[PDB]
Amino acid sequence: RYTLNATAHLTMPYVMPGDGEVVGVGEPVAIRFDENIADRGAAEKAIKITTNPPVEGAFYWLNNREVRWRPEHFWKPGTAVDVAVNTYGVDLGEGMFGEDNVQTHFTIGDEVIATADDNTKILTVRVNGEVVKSMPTSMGKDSTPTANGIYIVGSRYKHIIMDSSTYGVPVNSPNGYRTDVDWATQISYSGVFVHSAPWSVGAQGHTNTSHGCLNVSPSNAQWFYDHVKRGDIVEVVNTVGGTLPGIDGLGDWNIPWDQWRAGNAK
């Protein structure tokens, strides 16, 4: 027990969520190393997770330095999770060892699930199974459509600039953009946000005009930004698009329990 808490040569682990955070029902526990991990099974073995009420869960790797852990279903509101990353000096393979141990405790807030349905072009926000907000929306147009699936709410911004080059699409090109936006809530690592779009209010509710983001009105975007937290859920249904890769970053729930469970330790 020479521990360090997770605030929100060798390899350091970094665990999300951070100590004390309150997170939405889809927040997976995340352990991310600063080095690639030859011996996944080892790293998994060194990570103890307790939950109360107890719930079964399992590890799946998003890449070679990041493991994730989650239940089969969304968390039940109330659950406390404690994470013990007992990795100090542990054999992680090919001459790499855990630099230290790491701890975190977190808790699960309300069930918040927002469904965007391309049939109606409404994004309906549900807190504990009840409709508290209904927002006309406008998504990827057919030629750059919004992927179907379940997205985990990641970070939030009062203002930023989305630049398509970040995703290997030049600004000068036909799907290019470098756009200033307010009240931006990120929901995929591939660049999908729910955000203020005063330029598509006319279209919100009628027609997809965006590059992929869920355009909503300025006050609904602000509302989304005020009431939403990491781990809350946006589900997108019925678009002409594909499915959001399970290994996106915020795609976890699109892998099915069974593929997930089986893990990918090797």
Image: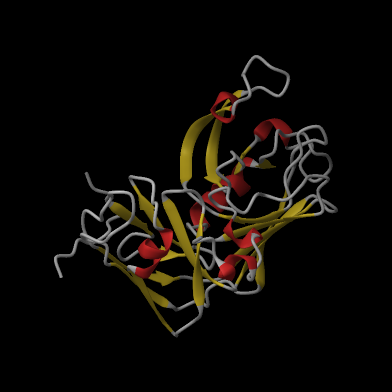
Left or right: where 217 falls relative to 52: right
**Up/down of 42 relative to 197, above or below:** below
| Rendered residue at 30%/63% (across/down) | 19
Left or right: where 16 falls relative to 233: left
In front of the other: 179 or 1: 1
| Rendered residue at 76%/42% (across/down) | 204
Residue lying furthest bottom? 53
Residue 109: x %, y % from top left: 47, 70
In front of the other: 80 or 67: 67
In front of the other: 163 or 112: 163
Q: Give the quadrant of residue 208.
A: top right
Q: Give the quadrant of residue 49.
A: bottom left
| Rendered residue at 73%/37% (across/down) | 201
Left or right: where 253 falls relative to 2: right
Residue lying furthest front? 94
> How does the figure colour the protein chain or chains?
secondary structure
- Quarter of the N terminus within the rendering: bottom left
Q: Give the quadrant of residue 93.
A: bottom left
Q: How many marks?
A: 0
In front of the other: 55 or 262: 262
Residue 227: x %, y % from top left: 51, 58
Residue 73: x %, y % from top left: 60, 73
**Up/down of 91 relative to 107, above or below:** above
Residue 80: x %, y % from top left: 39, 77
